[PDB]
Length: 302
Ligand SMILES: N#CC[C@H](NC(=O)c1c[nH]c(/C=C/C(=O)N2CCCC2)c1-c1ccc(Cl)cc1F)c1ccc(F)c(Cl)c1
Ligand code: NA
Image (tube, rainbow, N blue to C red; front, side, top):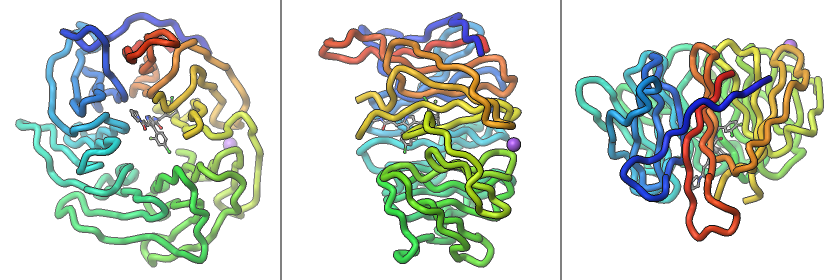
């Protein structure tokens, strides 16, 4: 895969830039950029200009997820309460609900009517409308205690992976524990609905057998392109930039290695657009020994 840098966004009216995460708007107009002070900046991709600034947190934004319908946004931050929140993005920018001690959140996938939050080894499922906690998912007997566990729904919303344990949501119980082969990473569902990727191990969802071991995915966070044909993986720094300077691409259909991309700067986040046209990467432009970070967003043609 080739990645041509075409633009750079820098926190305007500032000496050093403080972006920490990125997501493309559900409709193609904006790049949403979270900052190290807890703001969310909306940049017009075409004009290159900031058009809005929203107040979300009082510490660095760690995670952004826009709903597909364009109406809602999840955020997470690093140490200020609430650690996660849900925002409405219609006429007014509103906090709809917060998830005060959950340090990571995602939407449900099939129908975006729920949020799943993670607090340590525990998952919480919330109703978007009421904000009420519907489920708590934790089994002390099956737990892997992954240090960087993040809970997630599968594509049809009927299963959750939490701490390497598969849960049936409708009957609220664990159905399988995947064996523990690392200390940190808890895994994700492939958008195809057929595999679960837990660190270096690719598991078959139908039979639960190990299909592949991919050493290059060790300690990686993973994201797919819109059509689910390319998987991006970047290795976390040992637990400050969350990643090192490289990410790798794989063909999502057979896991075939594509490319290693080293931008020679530490990476804070990576996001893809809906049209498979652009990749945005938050990169520390600052020198190795600089006292302060200078994290910009670089836009790449895919
Ligand atoms: N969403 C999304 C995209 C996803 N981003 C992250 O995973 C991500 C992006 N950022 C933080 C964390 C900041 C953080 O802790 N900070 C930043 C400022 C101070 C502390 C995390 C992150 C790290 C650990 C955990 Cl277990 C989960 C997290 F979401 C990603 C997927 C593939 C990739 F190739 C890349 Cl480069 C990124
Ligand atoms: Na496949």
